[PDB]
Image 1 (cartoon, helix red, strand yellow):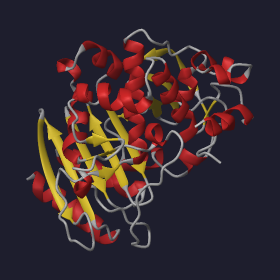
Image 2 (image 1 turned 60 degrees about the vertical axis):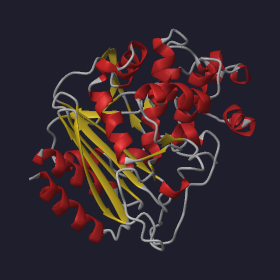
Image 3 (image 1 turned 90 degrees about the horizontal axis):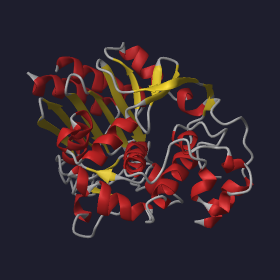
Image 4 (image 1 turned 90 degrees about the vertical axis):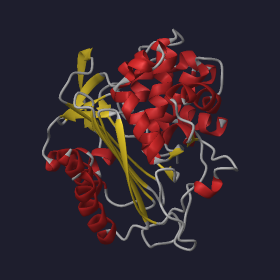
Amino acid sequence: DIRQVVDSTVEPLMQQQDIAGLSVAVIQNGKAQYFNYGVANKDSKQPITENTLFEIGSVSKTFTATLAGYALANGKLKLSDPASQYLPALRGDKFDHISLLNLGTYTAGGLPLQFPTGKMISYYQHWKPAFAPGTQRLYSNPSIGLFGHLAAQSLGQPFEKLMEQTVLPKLGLKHTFISVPETQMSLYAQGYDKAGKPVRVSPGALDAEAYGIKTSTSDLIHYVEVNMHPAKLEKPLQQAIAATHTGYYTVDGMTQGLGWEMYPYPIKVDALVEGNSTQMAMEPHKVNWLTPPQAAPLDTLVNKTGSTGGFGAYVAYVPSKGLGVVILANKNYPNAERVKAAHAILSAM
């Protein structure tokens, strides 16, 4: 049944892309299944399992967004608030008329894909917007980076503390980390670059917010499951998850939430791949706001891509169907291949 379709999509994928290790998790009706291939380390030949820890890159962005949503559920913040409101050092002009919403949906006005502490603050102070806030989407790590920081500020605690001592335990995730603890170190997969060379993500400002989470398929498919079915979560988390799956604007058939991107389901794999493409990340796109932001409706696909130097993560699920797939690899292989494989598995389910 499922095990054979997953095997016949991932094995050829892994051979084609020369991936050392791949774990896949699917969920249906609250029930998870794990399909594990290859090795976490090419030297040790440590096998991949659903407890293997991977870097998930920009999928971290959904965790950041849930953190911000938890701050809003607890009255610490409004999405319309100006960013300067939460950081004195940014007061003076610019960030007085850029909203938190703007920062979180990448519409702050031209913040770049990546950074060229307070020296990152200084980056922001010297930054010259290319466009009016709210007019164009430009995928940017510093934008969601500051979104998370500010959301942490509002709650009077540092990002890392909030995430690990508050937000993740309350999601039931005990194998999701910003910093991989010493006892779990051996579970941390080795990442390999385009050439097969080992590499782990390198620290950076507000990395924790943008691309700094690592987790296993077991914890990430659970994350996916409570994002689909939040009714057992405490109320502020429920409200938070509603906030992240709210659509605030459209950009080419894709409707933007907080961290999560959303599409009609079903969708052609071709429509799904072009929505996750290289230029839909690197090119600026004008945005049709939703004058009344739209609560999550049925027949929607939720997905997220995320990459590091040596890792390739992808998440896709359709909440109204209760269907979710997670694929974690210790290779940054192309996005198109990730959605193709996810799409196949979801269909078969």
